[PDB]
Image: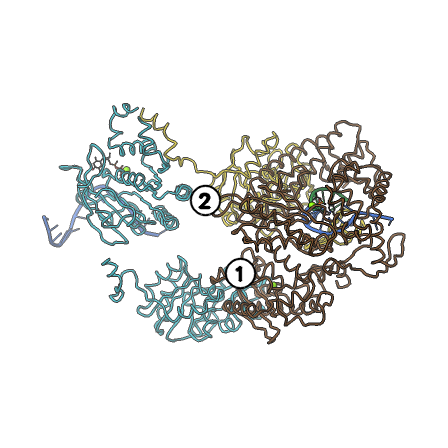
Chain colours: A brown, B yellow, C cyan, D green, E blue
Amino acid sequence: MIVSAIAANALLESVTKFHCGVIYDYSTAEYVSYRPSDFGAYLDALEAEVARGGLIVFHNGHKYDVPALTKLAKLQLNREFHLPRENCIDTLVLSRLIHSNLKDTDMGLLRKLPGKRFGSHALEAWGYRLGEMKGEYKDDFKRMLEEQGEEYVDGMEWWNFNEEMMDYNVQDVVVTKALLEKLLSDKHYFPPEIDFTDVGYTTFWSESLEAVDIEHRAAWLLAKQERNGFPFDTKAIEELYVELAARRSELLRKLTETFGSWYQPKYTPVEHVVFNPSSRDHIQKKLQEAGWVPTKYTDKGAPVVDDEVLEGVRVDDPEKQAAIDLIKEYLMIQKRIGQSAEGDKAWLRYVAEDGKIHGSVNPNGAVTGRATHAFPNLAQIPGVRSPYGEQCRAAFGAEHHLDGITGKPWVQAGIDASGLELRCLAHFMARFDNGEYAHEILNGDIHTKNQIAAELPTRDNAKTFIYGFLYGAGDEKIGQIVGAGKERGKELKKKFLENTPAIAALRESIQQTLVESSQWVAGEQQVKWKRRWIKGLDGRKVHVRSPHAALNTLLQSAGALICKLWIIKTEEMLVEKGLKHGWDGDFAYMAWVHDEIQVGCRTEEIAQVVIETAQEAMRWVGDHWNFRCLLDTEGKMGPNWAICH
Amino acid sequence: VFLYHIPCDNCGSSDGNSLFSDGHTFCYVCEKWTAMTYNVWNFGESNGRYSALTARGISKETCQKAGYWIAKVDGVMYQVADYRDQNGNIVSQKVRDKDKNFKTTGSHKSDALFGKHLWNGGKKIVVTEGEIDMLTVMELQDCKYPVVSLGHGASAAKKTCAANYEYFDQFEQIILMFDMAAQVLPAGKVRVAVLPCKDANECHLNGHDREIMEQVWNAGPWIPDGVVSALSLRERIREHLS
Amino acid sequence: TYNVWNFGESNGRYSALTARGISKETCQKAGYWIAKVDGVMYQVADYRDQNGNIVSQKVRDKDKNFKTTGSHKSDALFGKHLWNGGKKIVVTEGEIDMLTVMELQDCKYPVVSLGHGASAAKKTCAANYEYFDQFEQIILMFDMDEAGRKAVEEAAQVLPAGKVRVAVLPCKDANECHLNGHDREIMEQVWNAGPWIPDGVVSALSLRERIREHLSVGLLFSGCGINDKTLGARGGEVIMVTSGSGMGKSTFVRQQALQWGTAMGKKVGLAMLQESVEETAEDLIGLHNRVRLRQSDSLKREIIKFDQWFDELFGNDTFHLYDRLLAKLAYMRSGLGCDVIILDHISIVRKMIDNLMTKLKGFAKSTGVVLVVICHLKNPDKGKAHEEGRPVSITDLRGSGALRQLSDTIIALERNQQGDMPNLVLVRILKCRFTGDTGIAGYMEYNKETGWLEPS
RNA sequence: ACCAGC
DNA sequence: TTAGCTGGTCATTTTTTTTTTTTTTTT
Ligand SMILES: Cc1cn([C@H]2C[C@H](O)[C@@H](COP(=O)(O)OP(=O)(O)OP(=O)(O)O)O2)c(=O)[nH]c1=O
Ligand SMILES: Cc1cn([C@H]2C[C@H](O)[C@@H](COP(=O)(O)OP(=O)(O)OP(=O)(O)O)O2)c(=O)[nH]c1=O
Ligand SMILES: [Mg+2]
Ligand SMILES: [Mg+2]
Ligand SMILES: [Mg+2]
Ligand SMILES: [Zn+2]
């Protein structure tokens, strides 16, 4: 087992040059350094450690470091260099599962950290937390150039090689080794009956938990689909921007003549301030002086203003009754513009040269094992029920990738699971009601018949209501779904509690398992805990934030892991079936939002093979962990991500 | 840039106040933000107020971000526009009123541009001839895209645009709004838009502002006058020998 | 500017250069240091005479400005006082290059540098001839630019002969090759270099394979001879056509423009300034169909079948006519993809002609387009004129004399106008850079009925 | 405080 | 006594022509 550290010139998007690299070994204890001219020797050392059957320890190695080596070894000296995924291990993917909760334990330490490093899994932040940090390269280089007198141009100091870079690379691999010893000094994930610094890739993976293996496979696959990208159409979103940027410049002209300006106190100094519809103070004032009473006081002196009170508002003047609808449309158009094209993290500021969007996906960002999406967020674009939704999802298509050998577009397949957490509930409470609840879910659709039984208008409203009732609501927040009062908010709770009297028994079981005493304060809550964590489906200590969200962190943390294994198995069957992953093959993953997957493939027969084998992968997931239910999915085929929603 | 949330101290919230890399905090509940003449006119001396223009249409934040402020000195109304440099310091001023009493104070250079102290990287740029059309484009684009304007008029374009060559070299596409023609800029980069009105404000005040924005993102490349190809000349050869 | 900056009155400190690649020992040996005056740190280099007295400062700031502390002499080299002899020196272009050479040679070789650069190298290398007598070999280390090649070419007259070699570099200069790790290729360029060989001195040893290459085309010309001698036209060449007034320059270049758009199929961009656009197209239509058009009244109205003769030759997008001019020609090269650019008259476009010819030469060097430029001749002071059969010399170029120093080939035409027959021209090649040979190419006749210069 | 997702 | 998990938002210096006289090969 060796511990390697790299340093190159730029990010993985545009990297062309190698600068330095340090290797430490666990059998000779040698800081074997390398130079810019020793890159062949560096690759030979890594290939020797692979060929003898060992493990290479990087940090952030799956996302950046290993494909940087595969790119540099090709485009600098013309040689193929691939590391097998069962040899490379990471110490960031291990940190995101072992220390999954830094924001709730990092206070009391901020005396150590500067303040910008609060809750960071970066390698320098663990240098500050382990009390082993000797300077920083960027600060010392900036201080050096200000001491010489030449300017500091762009914050790009990895242009030229020097000797301080090697020293801070040595300190970097020191911090990586001192992190690895603590991360392997854990006992719940690594049993203390064997030393993990001399075992092979058949002992290290399969003589420990399954959560240490599934997380590395997920990080590998999600880094690969991050490197693939998402095909994007630019002209069809510039047409949308030029369409609805000539609408908010009419909804203000038509509206400031209705709602006039006023003098507001800044001898009494006044200023001529005009009506700004994006503010929620000007609309509150102009509705206060036009004859409207809120009768809803969230704030202690101000009302609440949102889309559910701008519908139930009536005034005397019949012009303002039409003006309020234009105010709501103006707020919608403003949010649409700021998301699509004018924001700091807009869509048109993260399009590469080849017409694709690369978004970072953190596989373990939530406390319940749910992935987060950032820079930009491709799990937050407007759906097909919101206005201007289909015109925003039609640009995010897979038919915008014309093929590089025949000049033809591709086909997209999208696969969604059905009734995921609601069927995990029937898994978990099947030991109470003897499994006569997990038979009605398999007998026809669940949400449609729930809508029939509860006389909700839409299936989406029934689906919102059932999880709102299930994850511990109050008396009003499920009466608000239909708009009625707390009388209906009580009778719906009684109706869906007296049907299956096992949810309260399961909740009492969770309360008797986790909490033992909870003292009551008139403004707070003081609880003596017994077990703050919950064993998940693969032994991972899932952290619990509040004792009334215990059913939540028991259901969604067990629902995310079956999707996380399903996305791995549905390519482990496709590669073994005789296909090729990537753009130069037959299929490519594009995006993984919390439930469904979006894959793009070359022909319709390959689409049919993928949409067949997704079912077999999901059934193998359902058989591997011995669920008491029967898991099932549903797939669609199309050109873009508006039919394949 | 956004980092995380801190608990606020005025409104008492927990996830309302946000911390940033610049050092300032901002709450979203209580909305509290924490931490010639040769005479440059002070903003507080001549009673500088950030007012708006009603008959043409310019919001207050555009005048706050562009440096176009109204003075109430000596009982009259002045519209002072400031010119800045790449370091972010006040260089010169221009005073415009109803009688067009131009008072150019300070060291007015031969390459002065309005709106260059905030915008250095990008792909497109819109170059206009005045100050009202430039603020109109900043109103239509919400003050977030690189738009500059000539501070010397559309008659001396061969001096201001020619002296600024390395500044316009940093961009990929330059789109002009002069007259509805310059060759000192490099080729394959100059685009000229065609408006059905006099300028941008005539399209803004008559409902043609959509045809402003359609000529910003879908402009055409100027093909310099008279370089007519031999194919579109049949009528001028038929009438010549007849 | 004021006085020689002492290190006590300016807080002098000797440090290294991290971002450039120079340690503190090299700047300590040379005398390069940094002062703290007026807040901004100012870097400064020291100049010393032959004795060793402090005579000049060079002050540079973080924004690349120049500040000479006083009277800057011409015999002051950066690195001159430390060495007073040797067998091999290395002449660089700047001051950081000399520090780079001292760093990569462990302070062994006598290495000097220039104090002016590639702009005033002649002034600092002509007056320093008495210093270069005590040396045995000189290795020139200039930039890989156009100005560096101009400096190493124009420095061939003020240096001693038989001792100075020139080295090449793949970087801009030695500093980027020091930063990119090319420390094994600069020593082979210091130890081994190439001799001068200025433009005319070909040794007999260097003909081992050139005679075999001699014992082994481009755009051809129409009408007899010419392409047999100058081997046709190439990319980047500037062809000149000089003749007397009325000798047939426009007809010859129009025939060359017709046969490069109907046979070679290349895009040809015309520019006629002597006439309008409604006449040259009619002349091309009359020239293609073997029947003279603009000199017959009945046939101009008899054919008006005009559209057939129009789209037979203008059916494609081949030709591009024209009715400050360098932007037009740059659009004709880039925005249209033309291969041939013809300029009909240059005198209507001393200092103006030279600047215009340098600008056209830079345009033809950057783009790589076939360029034909037509000018006129002088007025002879004794003898016959150029219209009765006097051979055109290379001296008679109308305007500032430098029309031949920036061209590549010159073709002249002579015919006896007031004589026995005016329809037998003589073509004379005056200068060819590639082939070299000059003289009479061939003989053509005009054939008054048709208009084609057929050979005879 | 608001909006969007799952 | 509390539907939940995330993101994203705002701001003080040498070129052609004319015309008089002294001397030199060549056709
Ligand atoms: C809508 C919703 C879902 N969830 C959880 C449970 C859902 O199963 C999962 C994804 O939601 P959905 O995919 O929208 O719902 P579903 O999969 O049960 O139904 P179907 O696919 O047949 O249309 O996330 C919430 O926690 N809160 C919510 O508001
Ligand atoms: C060469 C040649 C031309 N001509 C004709 C062709 C033209 O119609 C006319 C004159 O030739 P042109 O080519 O027209 O003369 P030009 O315009 O190039 O001259 P410049 O620009 O210097 O003023 O003479 C003959 O008759 N016999 C010949 O041998
Ligand atoms: Mg690293
Ligand atoms: Mg689903
Ligand atoms: Mg002519
Ligand atoms: Zn607050």
- Where residue A192 sits: x, y (%)? 72, 71
Quadrant in the rendering for residue A277: top right
Label 2 element class: loop
Q: Amino acid at mark 2?
A: Ala
- Where residue C456 sits: x, y (%)? 17, 41
Give me the C-alpha separation between circle 1 and circle 2. 39 Å
> Residue sitting at 59 percent across and 76 percent down?
A28
Q: Nearer the viewer, residue E3 or B218?
A: E3
Q: Nearer the viewer, residue A596 or A481?
A: A596
Judge from the rendering whether residue B231 lies leftward or rightward of residue B69; answer left or right: left
Which of pointers 1 and 2 indicates the residue nearer the eye? 1
Tell me the tag on residue A70: 1
Q: Amino acid at mark 1?
A: Thr
Provide the chain ID for the residue under circle 1. A
Up-down relation of residue A94 to residue A567 (above or below): below
Provide the chain ID for the residue under circle 2. B
Up-down relation of residue C395 to residue A47 (above or below): above
Label 1 element class: helix
- Could you tell me if residue B59 is visible in this image? yes
- Could you tell me if residue B44 is visible in this image? no
Q: Nearer the viewer, residue C451 or C114?
A: C451
- Where residue A169 sits: x, y (%)? 59, 68
> Residue sitting at 49 percent across and 38 percent down?
B220
Q: Which residue is mark 2?
A: B187
Which quarter of the frame holds ligand 5? top left
Answer whether labels 1 and 2 touch (C-beta < 8 Å): no
- Where residue A272 sits: x, y (%)? 73, 37
> Residue sitting at 27 percent across and 65 percent down?
C206
